[PDB]
């Protein structure tokens, strides 16, 4: 039913996968300053700079957590 578990990392695939080490959206949020609401709703509002915050934690690219959304893009 639409929802959001399409091709992107499920809501738990994001935190479960990241937190698999020692990360939590509440920590990445206050670590830069943006309140938790910003980072949270950063999963739907067009704002790839907030995705860099999360991907920055895995030292990877946001294109890895949202594949079917980009296309060979950099």
Image: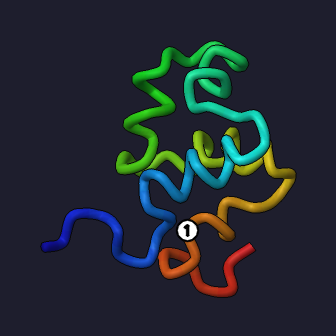
Nearest the viewer among 58 and 38 is 58
Q: In the displayed structure, does residue 14 sit left or right of residue 54? A: left
- Vertical order, 25 against 6 (above or below): above
| Residue 30 coordinates in the image, percent (x, y) | 63, 15
The number of callouts visible is: 1
Q: What residue is drawn where x is 49% and y is 46%?
A: 47
- Vertical order, 71 against 37 (above or below): below
Q: How is the image coloured?
A: rainbow
The local secondary structure at tag 1 comes to loop
- Reading the image, the residue beneath label 1 is 66
Q: What residue is drawn where x is 44% and y is 61%?
A: 10
Q: What residue is drawn where x is 72% and y is 50%?
A: 55
Q: Where the C terminus falls, by quadrant?
A: bottom right
Q: In the displayed structure, does residue 40 sit left or right of residue 31? A: left
| Residue 14 coordinates in the image, percent (x, y) | 56, 53
Nearest the viewer among 38 and 16 is 16
Dot 1 crowding, Cα within 10 Å, few <14, some 14–19, many 20+: few
Q: In the displayed structure, does residue 60 sit left or right of residue 16? A: right
- Vertical order, 11 against 64 (above or below): above
- Vertical order, 74 against 15 (above or below): below
Q: Where the N terminus falls, by quadrant?
A: bottom left
């Amino acid at each position: 039913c639409s929802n959001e578990k399409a091709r992107d990392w499920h809501r738990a695939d994001v935190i479960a996968g990241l937190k698999k080490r020692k990360l939590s959206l509440s920590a990445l949020s206050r670590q830069f300053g943006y309140a938790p609401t910003t980072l949270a709703n950063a999963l739907e509002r067009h704002w790839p700079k907030g995705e860099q915050i999360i991907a920055n934690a895995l030292e990877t690219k946001p294109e890895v957590i949202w594949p079917s959304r980009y296309q060979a893009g950099e």
